[PDB]
Length: 112
Length: 112
Ligand SMILES: CN(C)[C@@H]1C(=O)C(C(N)=O)=C(O)C2=C(O)c3c(cc4cccc(O)c4c3O)C[C@H]21
Image (cartoon, rainbow over all chains, first blue to last red):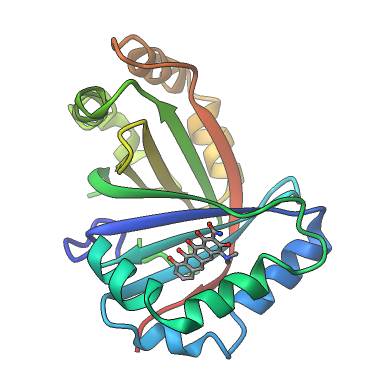
């Protein structure tokens, strides 16, 4: 969604510490895989964008949801979220567990 | 811009540690209170979205840029960037200097 779309009620920013660019590419490919297609159809899901840090040491997911309740009761309650968490957090090359920060959009500066 | 617009070549995620929700509100209010009106017309600036962490301890900015070159040359190299930093650090309730992570969008999941 546009970053300041009013439908975006909740945002998760998840950071995965990796040992380098080869692992960053694998992590992204696995996360945006094809078998993660079910996420697209979860009620309340708006977007998940994976980024590689410029220094090769981290992959960051910025994800937009309609609400915290949608994220917790529709994605979190689904058995596939536990499956995906296991898979991503056990890929070889990870230097620690993913760290998530949950947050609400409160203001935005955009060009006119 | 849409999170997966291909024009987004460079992203900065800046985390401001704060002492609770009241400071969260005051910092977003400051950041969107006109101190950075000038940024809207900077070439290559796409957006700056400020969010309050749900735990009350940080304000996070997700900022989209057309390229790292536009960010460094049209933002970082402009003396007004430093004035903006100084304005945001002068607020009571900040608990440390802001932390930045620089990154490139590499994959996305959108709805359907
Ligand atoms: C490893 N998986 C990928 C991982 C793990 O471990 C944690 C965690 N253990 O704290 C986490 O919070 C994740 C998280 O919040 C995720 C995970 C993927 C994921 C995918 C799409 C949207 C979205 O919002 C989201 C997400 O929030 C990946 C998570």
